[PDB]
Image (spheres, coloured by chain):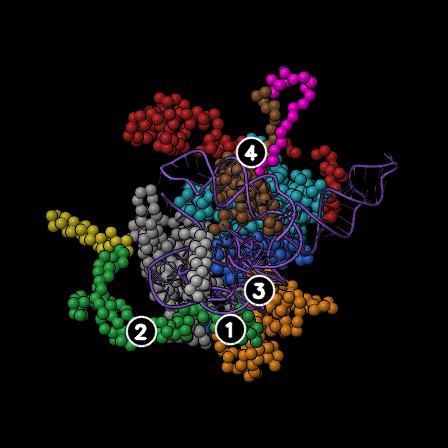
Amino acid sequence: TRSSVLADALNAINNAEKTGKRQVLIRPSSKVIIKFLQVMQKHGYIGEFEYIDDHRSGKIVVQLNGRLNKCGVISPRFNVKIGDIEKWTANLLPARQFGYVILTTSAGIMDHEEARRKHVSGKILGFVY
Amino acid sequence: MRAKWRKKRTRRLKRKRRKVRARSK
Amino acid sequence: GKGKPRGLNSARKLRVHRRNNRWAENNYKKRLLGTAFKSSPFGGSSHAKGIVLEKLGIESKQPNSAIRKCVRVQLIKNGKKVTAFVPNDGCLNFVD
Amino acid sequence: SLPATFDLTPEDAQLLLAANTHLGARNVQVHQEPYVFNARPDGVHVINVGKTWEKLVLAARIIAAIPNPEDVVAISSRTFGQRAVLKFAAHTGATPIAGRFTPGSFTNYITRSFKEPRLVIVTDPRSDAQAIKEASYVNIPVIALTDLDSPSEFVDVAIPCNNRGKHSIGLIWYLLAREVLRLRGALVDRTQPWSIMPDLYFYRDP
Amino acid sequence: GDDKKELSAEKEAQADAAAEIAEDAAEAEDAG
Amino acid sequence: MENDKGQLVELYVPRKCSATNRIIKADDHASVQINVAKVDEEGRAIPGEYVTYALSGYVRSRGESDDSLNRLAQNDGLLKNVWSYSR
Amino acid sequence: GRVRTKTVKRASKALIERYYPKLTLDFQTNKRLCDEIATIQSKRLRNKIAGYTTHLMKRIQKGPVRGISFKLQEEERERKDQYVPEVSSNGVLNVDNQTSDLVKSLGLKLPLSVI
Amino acid sequence: PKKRASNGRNKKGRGHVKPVRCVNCSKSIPKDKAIKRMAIRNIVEAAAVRDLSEASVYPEYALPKTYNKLHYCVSCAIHARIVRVRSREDRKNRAPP
Amino acid sequence: GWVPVTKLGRLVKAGKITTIEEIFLHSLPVKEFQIIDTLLPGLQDEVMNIKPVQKQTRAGQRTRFKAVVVVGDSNGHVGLGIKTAKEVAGAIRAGIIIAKLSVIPIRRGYWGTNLGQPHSLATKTTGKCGSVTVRLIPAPRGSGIVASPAVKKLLQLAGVEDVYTQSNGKTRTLENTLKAAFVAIGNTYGFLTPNLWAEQPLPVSPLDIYSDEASAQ
RNA sequence: AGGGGAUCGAAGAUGAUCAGAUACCGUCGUAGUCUUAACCAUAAACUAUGCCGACUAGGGAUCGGGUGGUGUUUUUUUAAUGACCCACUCGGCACCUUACGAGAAAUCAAAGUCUUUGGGUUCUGGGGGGAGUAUGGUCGCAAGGCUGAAACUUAAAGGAAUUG
Ligand SMILES: [Zn+2]
């Protein structure tokens, strides 16, 4: 059975981006999926997504625009402190000038740059580049 | 040697080891 | 996937699996079982003093053809009769 | 962007319909679903002759405005196409490989048949798939008169006609020659028809 | 024959036959 | 990319496929650049001014190059009704 | 048996390719031509060259070869290609039901029949 | 390696089938194996059609046929030329000649 | 006295094409090697490995020699050539020919803040050629090249200065290790970057521009 | 243990064959092959491919169910029904082309989505032997099964494919 809906969403996005499609359909939905795709959209990696709201969990269609090399989830959500963010970004970002590590922080879901600025840490969730 | 007959040879050796153990207590 | 457990509270299973596989490993098993002390001809030592019991000439292995001319010695601290190769030329004549 | 004279011209539409280009094959294929209009009973699919017409016009835009007109190449091995590609070769620049392709004609610079084109036209991709592969090796765009059940791999802009009709193949080659001439500039007064006539492009038995 | 240092063997022979045609040229110039 | 003074580095910017927005490699010997004619009044295609498209070897290999060029021709007005957005 | 080899076939095809107007249909004349327009070094080989040349010329004057082509052959093959026939009206267009549905969906005059 | 994708002959969703016996050696070979041919012959074969027609009462009645379903094992079929060794690409073809 | 055979050779002999940069930009097929003989002066070589290879015949044992060589100038262009020949000098020569046919560029980059003429790679990249993965990680300034000596010489001929290389698989096969590094250089240029997110007016095909001097004589 | 015992048939009796033939071949023939009640718990028990879940490529057949057809054939005047045809769909056993990818390769629509390394979870492996051996335990009427080393020894053993 479905253990990580974000992992299923990110696998679908990654597979269709490798295939070269311009859009994906993601089932089912979550607050964390919507907020993660919102961080993606704010940094410009994706285009525009629509949330189809049936009375079940719902679906998303995402209109991509290229420029998303790989999106991945880190299962399990690891308790990362403020001094291990640099270890994690060195481990799984390609270069130190681009790419974002997305943290599930008590101030919200955001990338490691906003985490460094707001001086707050949490559970590492995923990564985009 | 074929492994089947190797298994059979070790089987005879196991029987004889058990017999000689029972013989000498 | 990948077989190993990945959950956040699985570190007990990870430790148990690691201990069993370390027992499968060669050097770790030798060290913990202590075959250096239980079954080694030395007492886990680098060197050992023995005394020569005999001078034995043993043939080489194929394809080499020579007589290696080692000695048979008895260890003082254990009593285990071992066989030691005599080094470079004429030292067999040196050793009585 | 195209002006009003680049439409169907019903006077050319009866040429299409009388040459029976509208029929397709029994298999659809996923890259040719948009070209299929409807499924006639007794297992025939009809091809949108309108859609073939604007794909032909677009292919005319590709084939014309190549600055040296001879570097265009025309590939044929179907027995229903050699006369058509030779006539297209006569009217336009269009170096012809009517006949055998000699694998190694676009690479392998020491062959006598060594052509380095800038645009290929293929009469049939399934029966001429060697030339499409070689163009894929050496960076050449491909025009093809594909079918519904045609290989769409390694091929650019395609015009779905029949590839089973002698009249279809000949008339589509003729129409393409018409429009590349009328865009490059031998024939003016676009309302007027052409003096050369399609049964010239149609082949004989021998 | 030595399969593993043929590169140096042939380069040395290259220098040698270049030298031999050089003394051929020198002998031709000395005779002429 | 740049340096501290804004002086250009990256000896060549890569070309991007106009279908999938992916970098066209130097070794990509299937990727083709198509120069479509610019038609003014009654043909007369002006030499040197072409509407340009670039297709990548991946798009051609998967065989959706025809669909992509239908879409791009309709986006730039080369064609009117050849590609339907809703299949 | 009497199978001609690559030497005679290659030389005969090159000579026939570039010397078609001067060549004749007879062996004696053709072998004198080979003597003059070829610096061949063997007499029996020369006779073999001329014999295959004559046989290939017989086949050329009877019809086209798939091995080689000419400028006169190019002129005659063009003219036989632009032989032009008459037009392929029977009143209206032929029987049409759902392609007639296609033509009325697109919109054109197109006077046609039904099936 | 794996010579065949069918592992010799097709089972694909059974696990076990009842075996038959070969007709030349009586080897027990499974039914999905054991090359099966149909022998459709005449009792009154062509060397004697005219003989039996000229020596038979009931003029032009019929000519009977013999029907046999022959199971050959792999060794017996290879030895007795029913089946032939093939090349690597020709093993994939499964159309009768 | 070289003579062109192809349109690209005709253009570069005419001298209107003045750089491998528009060559690699328009992804033109390199079929001759004199084009970058004229266009890339000071393209020095290094033969990496000479290795005998044996085919067992009816009675003899036919031994050919396999030469793997590299070429590079000093900055950002590498070619890798493999040739098999009966004579090893001819193998080296034709390997130089093949490496010039297979010259490709690199994406040099920075480890941190952009200061003074990039030193390392752009992104963490990888290359796999036959159970050898060679992974190139950018490194800070002055750390040098850490690699096996063959990969180190390949990257020195590339002109990068600061690389960490990890490698897995049987790295003792020099041909596969060099091919994996070559694919890693290619993928280093092939990666997409937020610097490259911008849109360019798309180039204009110098063969099309200069087709009249590219025509037949 | 009891019943049944036709065929085939370990062991065996013979006749061949061979330098030898208590092997292959031929004749018989014990246990067994069948069954009732108890055991045993092993197989190349093999798809040599853990189970659950998602995505990624086209096609044509087939099994079971379902939907649509001013379709075909049947009664005795053509409706129902059944069977067949076409289109679609769900769930199966599979199959063909390609390689987008994967692989050391053979090959694989999964053995893909794996150095751009993290969906959940269980078991197993750490060069070849010694060895599935010795010992100890437990189950078994036994046959044996499950668990299971070390000393010592060796520089290879092996996988795929190519040329002879
Ligand atoms: Zn048999």
Which residue is under mark 2?
C42
In the image, the residue with mark 1 has its CB under 8 Å from the nearest atom of ligand 1 = no
Out of D128 and J107, give the one closest to the viewer. Answer: J107
The Cα atoms of the two marked residues, 2 and 4, are separated by 104 Å
**Mark closer to the observer (1, 2):** 2
* Membership of H67 in magenta stretch: yes
Q: Secondary structure at mark 2?
A: loop
- Circle 3 Cα neighbour tier, 10 Å, few/some/many (<14 / 14–19 / ≥20): some
Residue D18, image x, y percentages:
68, 39
Marked residue chain, label 4:
G
**Mark closer to the observer (3, 2):** 2
What color does chain H have in the rendering?
A: brown
Which residue is under mark 3?
A14
| Chain ID for purple | J
| Chain ID for blue | F
What color does chain G have in the rendering?
A: red
Out of A85 and F71, give the one closest to the viewer. Answer: A85
Q: Amino acid at mark 1?
A: Val
